[PDB]
Image: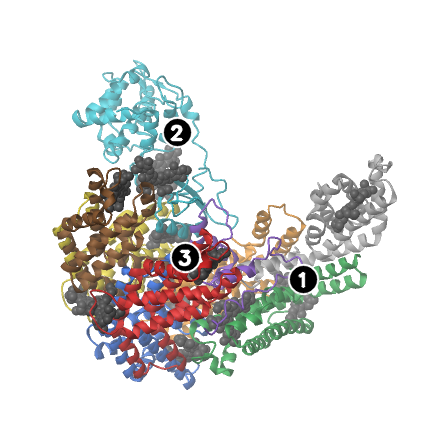
Chain colours: A orange, C blue, D brown, E purple, F yellow, G green, H red, I cyan
Amino acid sequence: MKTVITEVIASADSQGRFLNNTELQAANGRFQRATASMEAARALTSNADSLVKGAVQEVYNKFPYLTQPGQMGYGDTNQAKCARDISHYLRFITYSLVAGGTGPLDDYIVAGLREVNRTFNLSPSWYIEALKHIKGKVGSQLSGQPLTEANAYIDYCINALS
Amino acid sequence: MKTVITEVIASADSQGRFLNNTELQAANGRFQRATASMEAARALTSNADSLVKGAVQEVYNKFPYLTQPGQMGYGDTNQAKCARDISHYLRFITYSLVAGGTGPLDDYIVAGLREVNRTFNLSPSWYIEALKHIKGKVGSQLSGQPLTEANAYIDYCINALS
Amino acid sequence: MKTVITEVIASADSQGRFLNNTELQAANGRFQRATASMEAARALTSNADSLVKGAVQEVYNKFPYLTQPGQMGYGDTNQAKCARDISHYLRFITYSLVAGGTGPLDDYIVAGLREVNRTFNLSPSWYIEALKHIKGKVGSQLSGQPLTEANAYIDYCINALS
Amino acid sequence: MKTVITEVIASADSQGRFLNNTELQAANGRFQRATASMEAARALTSNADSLVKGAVQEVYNKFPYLTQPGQMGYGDTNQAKCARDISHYLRFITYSLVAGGTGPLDDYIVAGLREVNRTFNLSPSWYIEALKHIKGKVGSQLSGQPLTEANAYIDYCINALS
Amino acid sequence: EHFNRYHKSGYDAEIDSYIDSDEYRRVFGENTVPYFRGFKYQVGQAARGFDQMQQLFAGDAGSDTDRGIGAQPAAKLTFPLSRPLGVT
Amino acid sequence: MQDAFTKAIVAADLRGSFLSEQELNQLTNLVKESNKRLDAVNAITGNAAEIISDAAHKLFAEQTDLIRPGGNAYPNRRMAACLRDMEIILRYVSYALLAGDASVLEDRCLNGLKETYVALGTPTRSVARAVQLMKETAIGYVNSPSGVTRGDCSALVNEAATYFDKAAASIA
Amino acid sequence: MQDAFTKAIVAADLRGSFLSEQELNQLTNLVKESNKRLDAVNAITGNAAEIISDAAHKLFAEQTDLIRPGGNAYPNRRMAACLRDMEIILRYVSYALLAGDASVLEDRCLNGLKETYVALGTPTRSVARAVQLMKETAIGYVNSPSGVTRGDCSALVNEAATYFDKAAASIA
Amino acid sequence: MQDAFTKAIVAADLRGSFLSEQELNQLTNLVKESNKRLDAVNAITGNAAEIISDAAHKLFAEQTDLIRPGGNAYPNRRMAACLRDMEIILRYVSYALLAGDASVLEDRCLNGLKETYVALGTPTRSVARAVQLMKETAIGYVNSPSGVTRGDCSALVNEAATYFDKAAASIA
Amino acid sequence: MNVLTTSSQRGGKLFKVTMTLSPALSHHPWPSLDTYEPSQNSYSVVVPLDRLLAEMTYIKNKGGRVLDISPADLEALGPPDISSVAIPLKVELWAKADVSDVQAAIVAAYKQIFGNTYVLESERLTSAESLLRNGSISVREFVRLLAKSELYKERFFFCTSNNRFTELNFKHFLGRAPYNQSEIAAHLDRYQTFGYDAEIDSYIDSDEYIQAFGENVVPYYRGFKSQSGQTVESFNRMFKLYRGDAGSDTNLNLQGQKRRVDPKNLLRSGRGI
Ligand SMILES: *[C@H](C)[C@H]1/C(=C/c2[nH]c(/C=C3N=C(/C=C4\NC(=O)C(CC)=C4C)C(C)=C\3CCC(=O)O)c(CCC(=O)O)c2C)NC(=O)[C@@H]1C
Ligand SMILES: *[C@H](C)[C@H]1/C(=C/c2[nH]c(/C=C3N=C(/C=C4\NC(=O)C(CC)=C4C)C(C)=C\3CCC(=O)O)c(CCC(=O)O)c2C)NC(=O)[C@@H]1C
Ligand SMILES: *[C@H](C)[C@H]1/C(=C/c2[nH]c(/C=C3N=C(/C=C4\NC(=O)C(CC)=C4C)C(C)=C\3CCC(=O)O)c(CCC(=O)O)c2C)NC(=O)[C@@H]1C
Ligand SMILES: *[C@H](C)[C@H]1/C(=C/c2[nH]c(/C=C3N=C(/C=C4\NC(=O)C(CC)=C4C)C(C)=C\3CCC(=O)O)c(CCC(=O)O)c2C)NC(=O)[C@@H]1C
Ligand SMILES: *[C@H](C)[C@H]1/C(=C/c2[nH]c(/C=C3N=C(/C=C4\NC(=O)C(CC)=C4C)C(C)=C\3CCC(=O)O)c(CCC(=O)O)c2C)NC(=O)[C@@H]1C
Ligand SMILES: *[C@H](C)[C@H]1/C(=C/c2[nH]c(/C=C3N=C(/C=C4\NC(=O)C(CC)=C4C)C(C)=C\3CCC(=O)O)c(CCC(=O)O)c2C)NC(=O)[C@@H]1C
Ligand SMILES: *[C@H](C)[C@H]1/C(=C/c2[nH]c(/C=C3N=C(/C=C4\NC(=O)C(CC)=C4C)C(C)=C\3CCC(=O)O)c(CCC(=O)O)c2C)NC(=O)[C@@H]1C
Ligand SMILES: *[C@H](C)[C@H]1/C(=C/c2[nH]c(/C=C3N=C(/C=C4\NC(=O)C(CC)=C4C)C(C)=C\3CCC(=O)O)c(CCC(=O)O)c2C)NC(=O)[C@@H]1C
Ligand SMILES: *[C@H](C)[C@H]1/C(=C/c2[nH]c(/C=C3N=C(/C=C4\NC(=O)C(CC)=C4C)C(C)=C\3CCC(=O)O)c(CCC(=O)O)c2C)NC(=O)[C@@H]1C
Ligand SMILES: *[C@H](C)[C@H]1/C(=C/c2[nH]c(/C=C3N=C(/C=C4\NC(=O)C(CC)=C4C)C(C)=C\3CCC(=O)O)c(CCC(=O)O)c2C)NC(=O)[C@@H]1C
Ligand SMILES: *[C@H](C)[C@H]1/C(=C/c2[nH]c(/C=C3N=C(/C=C4\NC(=O)C(CC)=C4C)C(C)=C\3CCC(=O)O)c(CCC(=O)O)c2C)NC(=O)[C@@H]1C
Ligand SMILES: *[C@H](C)[C@H]1/C(=C/c2[nH]c(/C=C3N=C(/C=C4\NC(=O)C(CC)=C4C)C(C)=C\3CCC(=O)O)c(CCC(=O)O)c2C)NC(=O)[C@@H]1C
């Protein structure tokens, strides 16, 4: 899993060399940031649910036809799934904030994203809206660096999805 | 040349991906530290000379026989060289402080150190004393993080020499 | 470009050996089939247009919302493109029939399909319908082996798209 | 073992793809040809013996000295072997006709041919005559494609031997 | 082919693709250090083998170094590789 | 490798004999079916994507836990693998079907598969299940195509089954 | 590789001297801007996908022929490449922007690029165009972000430009 | 790679058009000749060894010096190469003949061959000569087989020639 | 072979793969027909999870075939600790044993006779236990009853091969592992004519059983310590037959009943038959 700390270790390990000042400087960077990151995670974790409801909802407004019978958005099972999925995205994001790297995101969400989505005919677009809607809400509960961090990670996914 | 900034770029580049939050965190670390680093360099640069004299000198006290005729420490040419050399070590150290990485040290000093030293029968020991003596003096002009940084780099060489 | 003939040459060539009876047998197969293949192509080529109209149309019936303003199906430019695109698919299919291999399809259509489609947000689904609708029409003008051939190639794309 | 069918599988398998129309066309070729091939085999199988006698014989006419004492052609053991060997060649040829590929020939006869022959001082020439004589006889019992097939394989060996 | 591989999957997969390539395995499966197979005819070779290998391989004193000026030199096989056949 | 023809040869070889006339007649008739045989294959390959897609849906509806955190098909990365694998198995099966022989399937594909699954902690049972799910869907197509001359494919259908089953068994 | 700091070092080295106080003050100042610098980069990376997407659309609206049969962006395969390339160039540019030095961009990306394009028959002109289109879009984001402390980024903005332009020039 | 069919396609593609009815009729008739075409190839492959053997004998009878000490075919090792080369060229030619297109031959076999020969110091003229010697022998077989239905092969014969000649020319 | 790292520098579970090498897969750079080094007939590689699929396909597409795959973490684990079996412990059932002592024996017997394998309340045998503790049955005789019991047959003898059942038997009834191919052959022939009961009888009846823990001693593990007339390799075979504490003989596990001792290893100790 890719976090700042793991990477410098890895790099040191490959070369076969002790951790020297170079790497520690980097580490120092992380952990300094953490304070903001951690704050952001506390905020998302708390409002989770509400964010999720709002998102799922949004998607339907954005793509009305999904809720029509014979579509994907239709019938509770699917709605349940839709909820579940977004929860996941969120969950991971928090993780990544705390871990201080994209690592968690990469391994759970991103790797294999395309093919899964292809085989089950999940349209990236949807997810994206979810995220965007989220981003917008988060853009109230947070501020300054905490906010900035939250965004970064949220986006990271947008880009991976698109 | 290995600095924090170059490394994260490199790592990003290998994976083939844009610089994401992971790397920036690291970079940030380098930049915040710089203030201390820079301070240290200003201090060494100024007292350079005095440090050098003191060191060279020390070495002779430590290894009296060097100054006897038919030895290496003997006759001005050699003394001049001895001075020159230590100057270099110092010079590079400053560089490394400023560059925020061992890079400068590795490429100028360390790579090829052994063989040079072997072929000309320069005893690592000597250099080491020089450094140690230096370290001790620096341990007065500096304090707190500035100091800490100075040490790190000075040591890094000790270890490479030994 | 992958056709029967090119492949056997390739395989022969890799091993470093003359074309022996093994390969010619294969070639013979391609040539015998051609008569049917060629027939199919003449049939598609002639009805091209009509097939295209029908398809494009279909897509809109299948996905009404596309024609609404602010969507992709909306505004003539897009419709023009939509037409163009399907034409292409067809064109290539004919090619492949005649060339006696998927080659033409692979190199024009398939390779890079995903990424193009991702970057411009073309939904595979659409294309698919187009094709299916086509397949259904073709299932009248043709019969026996000619038909069979037509299908094979049409499908090949369906699978690549999905 | 190299037959048409095995090869297309192999090629398909390497690229990691399903058997598509390209390969089936090829396969079809093998099967269509079979009818002729099979016919040829029935013909050789039946006249085997007679072909063998004739061949062995021929060789001796062509190279009288072989039958002199102290030579290879001399003394029954050797004659027996000589017979055996040619039988083999024939046997395999039939196999190859039926298998629809050189495969059987390659693996039994051809691979290692040279070294065997070198170490035991079997002169390729001999075998060749055998074959040629055969080819000539076969050129009566067969006709049209059946014939053509028979030749191909017979030759294939001539070339390998030479 | 390789440039695409690198863009999908990065330097590690790029490198792995040469060592795991069938060609590498057949000539020097395991237990054999790689040697210069160029300059002599290799099945499948394609002409241009010999000519391009002479550009990539200087003398035995030459090396592939960057130390002269930091950058590696430019490809030097791009123009070859894309030459038409001379009017027969 | 091997296939129906080559196989018969090899047998004959060890006896040291020309092919028996009886034995030819196996092959002679085998040829006659070719066309049927081909169409069968064509049907699978044509529907491939779908076959899988379908089977998967059903697999996950049954064994909900596979897709739950802590399950074997979670997260995405894993899911992807699971799909990929299914497909492969299918691919091979098809190959066999054309060859007219299990071998190819056994040797390239099935050999070592169980053990892999074991080492990973993949539940072999579920894998097997998937394979069957696939089987049924596949037959579905083989047996109900479009534009094909009407006739009896049973013989082929059963052989298809067997291949699927060898797979199921050796994995399981 | 190289960046602003390392560079200054190297210069100093050949003179054989400690770093001039004047020169330190370049770096000292450079540090102070860091935060700005970072955000700039962050902005690009965050919008990457879009930047490209956008630029492309505009590129193809202008030079219709690229996407017509016989053009260089046709067929799909080629199109894909063209997109890929754009992205890469961008990626590097960003890198440079962080480093505070063109080098990385020059050495990995720009060096030999023209000639490649030439050999392939890719029209260098159009490539250059794309790069600019990108430039403008990118600046767009760098310069108009959200939730960031307001101040002046011009200095950075211009340096960004230059990088884009070095690219445009050497390709062209 | 390329061949007769594929080629026509490609042309059509750049026009952006479905195949002309006229153009189909090229391919339609090309098919009809297949059988002839095949036999031609079969004839070469069947006689390969001989073709070479023969050509060589004649080559060395003419240019005695090649086989004299200090010549290019001396000693054994060199001789071997010379034979090997002949074969290769032949092999390719055949390939082309089947494809119905020079390309394959031009790209893998011919392109850069001259330069190689130059660098080695092997006398290009002699090589060319050999190629012709081969040509004549080969045609010999193509044109005079046994058990083939008698008819006109000229068309194919000439195309064969051309291939050989492209070779001769580009080497020379 | 030993694997030195469990995981790659990039996170990734390494997996040891064992194949039969083929000339194509590796060959000497020598003139003449390609030959793999004889010593590496069975080659082993440790690959990260990512390259595992590619690695295995390539092996199989050549004439290679996969002998087995195993996670590197299970591999590169200590050989089991022999602490508990170095000195078995031993249980004696005195005459006029009080209630507890009889219980201890029973437990111990089930442990050794069945392996770690668990015996459920319903599986347990009241009748046999009944007899012990009002006299009438020897510990030796109880042991016979257990090996006669279906419980025993269902686990050991009805799932695995008779080849496997023999050594399975050896270990339970005698601490020893089997020495030599002959022992395995003798038992197999006994089983074919006499049947299952006679074979079971022949281990308890054997003097080796009598000489150690002859009567009224629960069998203990003689193997893992030096025994008379025991081939040195038998000691190694005991490490294969006995894997750790909390490792059992289980029909239950996937492909449960297999051979711990390869036939070839038995042949080394002795051949003749
Ligand atoms: C929400 C916008 C839409 C929606 C979603 C939806 N998802 C599925 C099925 C799956 N969703 C995922 C996604 C994930 N699973 C994971 O493990 C992860 C990573 C942690 C993600 C992001 C997966 C894998 C599936 C496949 C099967 C499964 O449920 O696990 C469906 C069902 C579609 C089907 O037929 O299989 C749906 C509908 N639901 C909606 O209503 C929105 C349109
Ligand atoms: C000082 C503690 C002792 C001493 C030193 C001394 N050094 C040399 C010669 C060399 N010393 C170096 C060192 C460097 N040159 C470099 O380029 C670098 C990297 C930037 C270093 C660290 C080198 C390379 C030389 C060899 C070439 C040269 O002529 O400088 C000598 C002379 C040895 C000789 O054989 O002439 C000496 C004596 N002198 C003292 O008094 C101390 C014992
Ligand atoms: C039709 C089902 C829908 C539709 C299509 C549509 N396509 C585009 C843009 C492109 N379509 C393609 C496809 C191809 N171009 C090729 O070169 C090939 C291979 C020969 C194919 C299959 C491409 C590449 C483009 C992108 C570049 C271009 O402009 O051609 C659009 C425009 C979308 C955009 O500009 O972002 C549209 C709308 N239109 C409809 O009405 C259907 C929904
Ligand atoms: C017949 C034209 C001449 C002749 C032949 C002859 N052969 C041998 C010995 C061998 N012949 C072969 C050939 C094969 N063995 C195989 O397995 C195969 C593949 C199916 C072939 C083609 C072999 C291998 C041997 C070597 C040893 C053996 O026992 O086979 C001999 C004996 C020579 C010797 O040195 O032992 C002879 C004489 N006999 C004639 O009269 C003709 C001149
Ligand atoms: C899907 C129905 C089930 C599933 C599959 C699954 N597989 C893996 C991982 C691998 N599976 C294989 C498969 C093969 N190895 C071979 O040799 C062949 C035949 C040629 C196949 C088909 C392999 C090699 C792997 C390991 C390497 C890889 O990355 O694929 C996983 C992932 C395991 C992990 O921990 O990452 C999964 C999930 N498992 C399920 O949940 C389904 C029941
Ligand atoms: C069997 C599952 C179903 C079925 C099959 C069936 N097919 C035919 C006949 C033919 N099928 C083909 C198809 C091909 N031949 C080829 O060369 C290729 C590869 C390019 C294919 C795909 C052909 C050519 C024939 C012969 C002509 C024809 O189509 O009639 C039959 C008829 C009997 C026969 O063996 O010829 C049958 C029965 N039909 C069913 O009812 C099943 C659902
Ligand atoms: C898009 C704006 C234009 C375009 C691009 C295009 N590029 C290629 C092919 C390649 N381009 C590169 C690019 C690079 N090589 C490098 O090393 C770097 C820096 C690291 C870059 C950016 C390379 C390697 C290739 C060659 C490999 C390949 O063919 O993929 C093509 C394809 C050319 C072809 O004929 O196939 C294209 C189309 N072309 C346009 O139309 C735009 C103007
Ligand atoms: C410039 C293009 C636009 C802009 C940027 C801007 N940023 C700041 C200040 C900060 N921004 C950051 C951002 C980061 N620091 C980090 O370490 C990281 C990566 C982990 C980021 C992304 C931070 C922490 C600061 C300092 C705290 C703060 O938010 O104030 C400024 C203020 C100037 C200064 O810091 O000296 C500015 C101007 N804002 C604009 O006006 C431009 C559009
Ligand atoms: C024979 C007609 C004439 C002859 C030939 C000859 N060739 C060599 C050496 C080489 N030949 C080649 C040629 C090829 N490389 C390719 O890629 C192809 C096909 C695409 C060919 C045909 C090569 C590469 C070599 C050099 C390496 C090698 O030996 O394999 C020689 C030997 C000369 C030397 O000094 O090596 C000769 C003699 N020369 C004659 O005299 C005949 C007229
Ligand atoms: C031309 C150099 C010579 C010649 C050729 C010729 N051939 C035929 C007819 C056939 N040739 C073949 C051969 C094959 N068909 C295959 O499928 C394969 C690969 C396994 C081969 C080798 C076949 C089957 C035919 C059809 C039946 C037949 O043999 O006649 C003809 C007849 C006319 C035509 O256009 O095909 C001719 C003329 N005849 C010559 O003059 C040269 C001797
Ligand atoms: C000949 C007297 C007997 C015989 C030999 C024989 N060997 C093989 C196959 C192999 N033999 C070896 C031997 C070696 N490989 C080595 O590297 C070394 C020296 C370092 C030896 C001695 C090997 C490894 C093989 C297998 C792989 C390979 O081909 O290299 C065979 C063929 C077996 C097969 O089925 O492939 C034979 C026949 N066997 C006899 O019949 C004679 C009694
Ligand atoms: C419960 C937390 C989980 C679980 C357990 C489980 N275990 C078995 C079977 C056995 N487990 C052991 C355990 C031990 N053997 C020992 O001697 C020790 C330490 C001394 C332990 C802890 C053994 C010996 C067995 C094998 C014998 C037997 O099964 O009778 C099973 C049964 C396996 C089966 O398929 O029958 C289970 C279920 N499994 C779960 O579901 C939990 C996660």
Question: What chain is tagged by disc 3?
Answer: H
- CA separation in Å, label 3 and label 2: 59 Å
Mark 1, other Cα within 10 Å: few <14 / some 14–19 / many ≥20: many
Badge 1 marks a residue whose secondary structure is loop
Between circles 1 and 2, the one closer to the viewer is 1
Of residues F172 and G36, which is closer to you in this image?
A: F172
- CA separation in Å, label 3 and label 1: 55 Å
Of residues A134 and H35, which is closer to you in this image?
A: H35
Between circles 3 and 1, the one closer to the viewer is 3
Of residues D87 and C6, which is closer to you in this image?
A: D87
Question: Measured along the vertical axis of the image, is residue C20 above or below residue H20?
Answer: above
- Give the residue at mark 1: G3
On whether disc 1 and disc 2 are found on a single subunit, the reply is: no
Quadrant of the picture in which ligand 10 is shown: bottom left
Indicate the quadrant where residue F76 lies.
bottom left
- Give the residue at mark 3: H84
**Residue D137 at what x, y percent from top left?**
17, 56
Badge 3 marks a residue whose secondary structure is helix
**Is residue G81 at all visible to an observer of this figure?**
yes
- Give the residue at mark 2: I239
Question: Measured along the vertical axis of the image, is residue E57 above or below residue D49?
Answer: below
Instruction: Residue at 40% x, 31% y: name it.
Output: I244
On whether disc 3 and disc 2 are found on a single subunit, the reply is: no
Between circles 3 and 2, the one closer to the viewer is 3
User: Ligand 9 closer than 8 Å to the CB at disc 3?
Assistant: yes
Outermost bottom residue: C76
Instruction: Residue at 57% x, 52% y: name it.
Output: A7
Q: Amino acid at mark 1?
A: Asp
- CA separation in Å, label 1 and label 2: 60 Å
User: Ligand 12 closer than 8 Å to the CB at disc 2?
Assistant: no
Q: Amino acid at mark 3?
A: Arg
